[PDB]
Amino acid sequence: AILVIAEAFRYLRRQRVDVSRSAGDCLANPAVPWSQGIDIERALKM
Amino acid sequence: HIDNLEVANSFAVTNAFCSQFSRGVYAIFGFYDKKSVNTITSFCGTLH
């Protein structure tokens, strides 16, 4: 799992994709997730 | 005090239950589903 996380972030860096967050309250309503979220997931799954 | 929520969403159920706890109610009448029943049981049991 650490191999996969390392690889995903090495990829996001390579691709000059940024990721910031902040973050705050998990029950904040709304309720708007960060846009980098999708890219991280995508980076993990590929 | 009535809240209307997506019972399948445990985050939303947590928010609703905790808001009622905050208000200081004697009991909460409500619903759960397969996805949220553990939120209800754990929160009820913990907060009494």
Image (cartoon, helix red, strand yellow):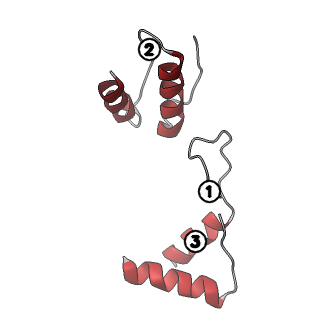
Q: Is there a contact, CB below 8 Å, between mark 3 and mark 2?
A: no
Question: Residue type at mark 2?
Answer: Ile
Q: Name the residue under label 3.
A: A40
Q: Is mark 3 on a helix, strand or loop?
A: helix
Residue depicted at 42% across the width and 26% down the height: B32
- At horizontal 69% and vertical 63% (from top left) the residue drawn is A35
Residue B3 % position (x, y):
59, 19
- Residue receiving disc 1: A23
Q: Residues within 10 Å of mark 2 (few under 14, many from 20)?
A: few
Q: Against A22, is A41 above or below?
A: below
Label 3 Cα crowd, 10 Å radius (few <14 / some 14-19 / many 20+): some
User: Which of the two discs, 3 and 2, sits closer to the camera?
Assistant: 2
Image mark 3: chain = A
Residue B17, x across and y down, in percent: 48, 25
- Are discs 3 and 1 located on one and the same chain? yes
Tell if the residue under mark 3 belongs to the same chain as the one under mark 2: no
Give residue A9's position: percent from left, percent from top: 54, 81
- Say which quarter of the image contains residue B29: top left
How far apart are the two marked residues, 3 and 1, measured between alpha carbons?
Answer: 15 Å
- Which amino acid, by three-letter code, is at mark 3? Ile
Task: Give the residue number, with chain letter if any, for mark 2.
Answer: B28
